[PDB]
Image (cartoon, coloured by chain):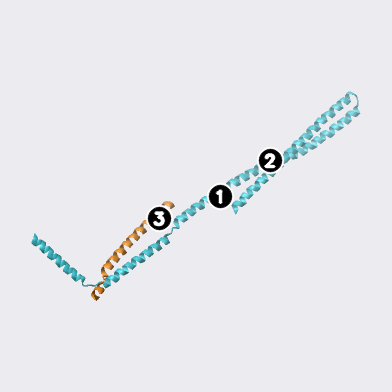
Chain colours: A orange, B cyan
Amino acid sequence: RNLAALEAKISEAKTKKNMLQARAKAAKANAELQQTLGGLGTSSATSA
Amino acid sequence: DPEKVLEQAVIDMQEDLVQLRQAVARTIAEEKRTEQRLNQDTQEAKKWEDRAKLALTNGEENLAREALARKKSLTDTAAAYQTQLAQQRTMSENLRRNLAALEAKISEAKTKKNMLQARAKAAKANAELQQTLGGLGTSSATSAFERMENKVLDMEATSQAAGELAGFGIENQFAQLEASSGVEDELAALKA
């Protein structure tokens, strides 16, 4: 019974962390795309 | 270690049961030898009685009484060896009963300790399995999740910093884009 509970805890913890890491990486990638789409070189164009 | 001490006690008991086997075997030989002595003394007592019968047949009562005095000495010596033998018989049975009790005590003590050691080892093995099934790495997993949560809070703080900064003209440009989309819908209605 301890082994069955241990395997369940390991499996759930591993898969939950893996999908959380994947979604966190996707979320920060989208945030950097929106930030870089905002942060255009408008001051350099204005200086020209 | 108590397991090494009780194993040494069982080894010492193997030496003791060999010493008691020797003491029994010696006592068995002493009873058999004193039986042999009294048996041959009583056969010599018969020879001296027959020597007396020969003397009486010849009329020599002097030699007959002398031969009967050898008979008396031999039968009294055989009675002394029977008395000595009675002490050997009781000692032989005492050592026999002590050996039977000793072997029973050794056998029971050895097997009871062996099964107690086996059950104690199985019990502590199960206790360590239940302890290790409880004692999982949950603090290390939580520390990894806390590092990811700190990076999520950095993205929330970055989103708050962008949200306070990003007040721009572009919202009025989106109202002009929606007006231009309305002109394309009016051109579509004209085409229809």
- Which dot marks residue A10? 3
Q: What SS does tag 2 mark?
A: helix
Bin the neighbour count of mark 2 within 10 Å (Cα to Cα): few under 14, some 14-19, many 20 and up: some
Q: CA distance from mark 1 to mark 2?
A: 32 Å
Q: Nearer the viewer, residue B122 or B57?
A: B122
Q: What SS does tag 1 mark?
A: helix
- Residue B142 lies left or right of residue B9; in this view the side is left
* Placement of B70 over or under B101, stated as above or below: above
Classify residue B175 by image quadrant: bottom left
In this rendering, which labeled residue sits more in front, label 1 or label 2?
A: 1
Classify residue B50 by image quadrant: top right
Residue under circle 2?
B96
Q: Are marks 3 and 1 in contact (CB under 8 Å)?
A: no
Mark 1: amino acid: Gln
Could you tell me if residue B96 is visible in this image?
Answer: yes
Classify residue B45 by image quadrant: top right
* Placement of A25 over or under B9, stated as above or below: below
Q: Chain of mark 3?
A: A
- Residue B129 lies left or right of residue B92; in this view the side is left
In this rendering, which labeled residue sits more in front, label 3 or label 1?
A: 3
In this rendering, which labeled residue sits more in front, label 2 or label 3?
A: 3
Q: Nearer the viewer, residue B190 or B130?
A: B190
Residue under circle 1?
B117
Mark 2: amino acid: Arg
Q: Chain of mark 2?
A: B
